[PDB]
Image: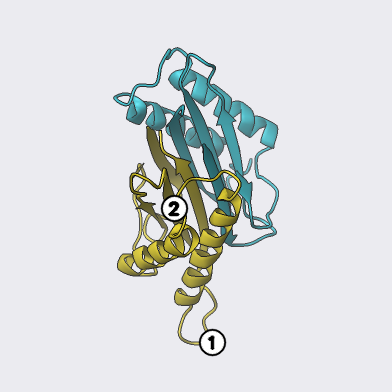
Chain colours: A cyan, B yellow
Amino acid sequence: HHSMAAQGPSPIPTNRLKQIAADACNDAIGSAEFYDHAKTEQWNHQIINTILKAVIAESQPSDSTTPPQFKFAVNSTIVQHLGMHSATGAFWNDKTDGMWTYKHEGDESKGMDVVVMLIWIAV
Amino acid sequence: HHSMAAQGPSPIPTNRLKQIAADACNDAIGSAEFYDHAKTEQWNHQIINTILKAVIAESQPSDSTTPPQFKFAVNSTIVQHLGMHSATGAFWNDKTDGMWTYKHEGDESKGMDVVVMLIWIAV
């Protein structure tokens, strides 16, 4: 994946985002030995709720006099192993808005990858 | 794909979004007989730029006294045929913000699908 659009700094340090996403994916599918189409919905739901709860919490201003300053969208995709190329463009505020993507690579026996993308939008 | 989050009406009628996306995909990969990893970047770039240009244009207020009211993000993914499940959650304004997704199904010989997602964010 690669962004076509210029962008602002993440309200959350990208090393923390990486940890949030890696932990979310691990909690959801870490013990899974195979891709199971019957569980992908449950898996994706758990990943997204985990990440969203974490980024909402940690993007909050320390003081009550300042309300949440960022909207977030979080997408999670589970892809069964085979060829995949993704791109993102935007019409937004290049000083403040942006995206970050994460790939949770499954090993040989896993038979699936998890790709996560987070968008933040100021105000 | 399915959204986990409640949402507002599209600033552009969804039948028009469907046409924009279908035409963009057709223009980019309509004449392609096979999946080619060496062309996916060019294909995705064309699709996204086409869609973005169209949605920017048609979301503009008719009057100059009112500036653009929506930010947009557009993601395009080209997937080689094999198992794929996607989900989206959000922390946004449920009265005004939302997402829309489109799948351009490739026939047997095509060997690839195109999935498009558009997010709109008020103000």
Q: Residue at x 36, y 28 (%)?
A: A40
| Total numbered badges shown on the rendered structure | 2
Q: Residue at x 40, y 33 (%)?
A: B82
Is residue A44 in sight in this rendering? yes
Quadrant where the image shows the N terminus of chain A: top right
The residues tagged by marks 1 and 2 sit, at their Cα atoms, a distance apart of: 29 Å
Q: Residue at x 48, y 87 (%)?
A: B63
Callout 1 crowding tier (Cα within 10 Å): few <14, some 14–19, many ≥20: few
Figure quadrant of residue A97:
bottom right
Callout 2 crowding tier (Cα within 10 Å): few <14, some 14–19, many ≥20: some
Q: Is residue A43 above or below residue A34?
A: below
| Mark 1 residue type | Ser
Q: Residue at x 53, y 74 (%)?
A: B68
Which numbered mark, 1 or 2, is in the foreground of this view? 2
Determine the secondary structure under disc 1: loop
Q: Which mark is residue A45?
A: none
Q: Position of residue B35 (x, y in %)?
A: 49, 45
Using the image, name the chain to which the residue with label 1 belongs: B
Horizontal side of residue A61 vs B107, given as left or right: right
Q: Position of residue B48 (x, y in %)?
A: 53, 60
Going from the N terminus, do you reach mark 1 or mark 2 first? Answer: 1
Q: Which residue is mark 2?
A: B117
Q: Is residue B2 above or below residue B33?
A: above
Q: Which residue is mark 1?
A: B64
